[PDB]
Image 1 (cartoon, helix red, strand yellow):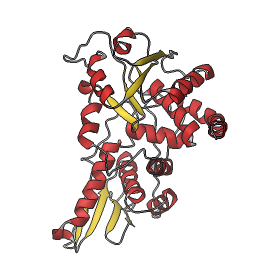
Image 2 (cartoon, helix red, strand yellow; image 1 turned 90 degrees about the vertical axis):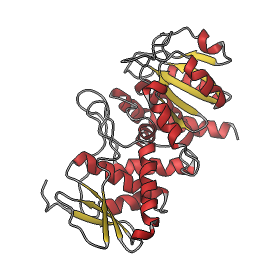
Image 3 (tube, helix red, strand yellow; image 1 turned 180 degrees about the vertical axis):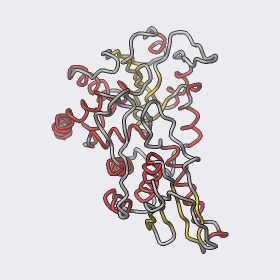
Image 4 (tube, helix red, strand yellow; image 1 turned 60 degrees about the vertical axis):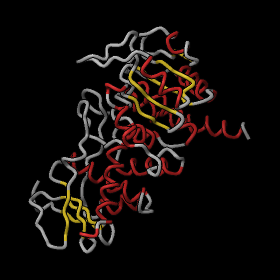
Length: 338
């Protein structure tokens, strides 16, 4: 909170990252640009990030674009951020993503570089009300982005930006692919549409088309019963209701049923609860820790980047706790199939 705490960090020979608490000075051979007011996080409650995949992908495009322009090839590109600690965490998050994804840096190396100036980044909070019981750091986000690359969760060579932005809007179904070709999360569908104003309650019909074309063969409902399962099954969808207390954690019986349904579905699975964030995100994170052996923090990070707001309150503790157990379940699983 003082232009004394200003800091410049080198990313590449031409790219620089700056945290300025004042007016960026200019220069004829330095180009300054900020995304503090360009790629903003749409918060639920006290959460302030991280930014979703779309914005991450947009940022990577802006960097590549700026490094390619003939008008600035002889200039240093400086990505600056201001005095808002939450904006700093996001801008730092984006540079980190760029190093991991396009540069070939490791999560640890990108993190080293980001804290070289001794900058003290505040860690990402959850979307619950009141005190946070768990925090995900920039390093936790870098490992997640890294593994998403290795396992095919992220591919900026094929990522469809307009598709991602179209379907996250409430008026189009508020949905997100968590794992491409395998897991989608969406807002609970209400029996009988109401796509008209103040509301954006979707009936199962605006999902059936998209679902079929992307091979969704299964549907799990964690929400309470707002529609008759029939409306989805009647279209060839296998449906399941693993109901359990809203905002609460799943019993192991439920976690095992979920993993069972999933481990056996024949295509992609669409999961939803009421907001398609908390309960939904919690169970999908479960499948990922067991099958990709990622930490609770890396998983929660990946899931929130795909669908901001996922995993809330006591849900985070649950994942953190169940981690060791899901890691081993997957261990045994992988070997049984061998």
